[PDB]
Figure 1: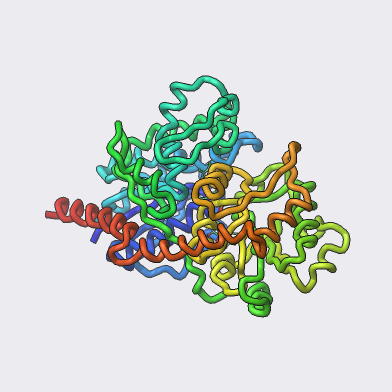
Figure 2: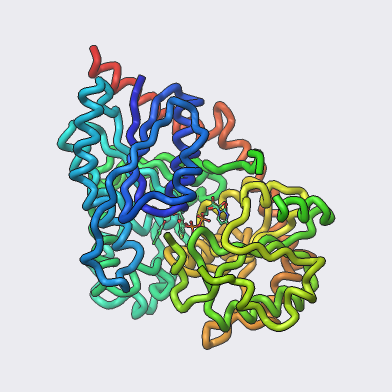
Length: 462
Ligand SMILES: O=c1ccn([C@@H]2O[C@H](COP(=O)(O)OP(=O)(O)O[C@H]3O[C@H](CO)[C@@H](O)[C@H](O)[C@H]3F)[C@@H](O)[C@H]2O)c(=O)[nH]1
Ligand SMILES: Oc1cc(Cl)c(Cl)cc1Cl
């Protein structure tokens, strides 16, 4: 049976959808999978747990940590994570040597959006390289266009006076392009660009999205183009929130249907002091029920990407006033279970794509609060094109004040404003079901890929 090797780049937002993708490969298609895990230090924590309790058809190899101690502590995350894959190639080659010895040379090597240098090892071993793309078809289009964009545009992107509007894509202002594009002199941009120039080497790109969610972008991506690999929407691949977990879910059990606003800023997002304070005050002001996963504030929006009690940062009396109607949990919540809970009615999110898909699958309307990476691009998509998210208004200084927090929260949870998005998410919840049926468009696309892999293995062994 084909053996697929999956090489994620660091980040829970990459490992989680890759684990869901692997489970579908083994359960639906009878393949075997090995995760090969690169890291700049020892594996977490959450990494070992997400890779725990998987069918025996899925194994994990943790590589020796690579040495990135030569890098500035101010190095951007995208540099760190791309380099982690790049510098792990020697160790990845040893793993592929063991696969050859075990009669299990992979049929494909699947990297994610920042791990294309692993293609060097795939090519050396005559293994087809593929990318699993954990974010939108809109942002995939941007990555595919980036080599041309880079060539044709010579200013920093924030200086563009017209928005970029790729075929089938929501327009995005240069100042809203994903964070690592925002400083072309930084190695974050060089690693972004380098990765995108390698996309044409992929035999196919599987994207965690679905037709009804991004119909125009998907149609455009699937049109033949110069050096453009085939693109397969295979989503939404999410944890549907049916696994066994506690205190926050007990609290949730005691709230009315559709009444709770879940608030979470991903696996690594934080707010500034000033913004954390205004958000807290606005949540309390709103008088809505809320479940907030809280991290300590920082001037760096992705500072917990990979300490202090976050509750010590909350304003005077905040925990007292909200003691019944609000549940504040430090660091991490069982998000899949929360979004699937009947008492959840809304989601204030950083627009991480896994959180977005989870919310879609459960029909939970959003407040779009982007922080870093490509989240702003996602927010513009979700609010202006898909129309399943409301956006808060930020002042000219970039702060979303308590009045606006309370306005948008009430608007989502009870207002006319929130009716449009709530209806839209209902339609998307239904379409998310449709596409993953035996003959749904996402299942068909994944099936075609798995069929290609089976045929490749067949021709090789015979
Ligand atoms: O308290 C918590 C918090 C999160 N989780 C789970 O962690 C995953 C969060 O992934 P998500 O894509 O929303 O955010 P993040 O990891 O910041 O995204 C990066 O990777 C994403 C994929 O490329 C990208 O769109 C984004 O911009 C990047 F920043 C998602 O499956 C949540 O259910 C949880 O269980 N409990
Ligand atoms: O998962 C990611 C996806 C994207 Cl598009 C960026 Cl820019 C950064 C991270 Cl960490």
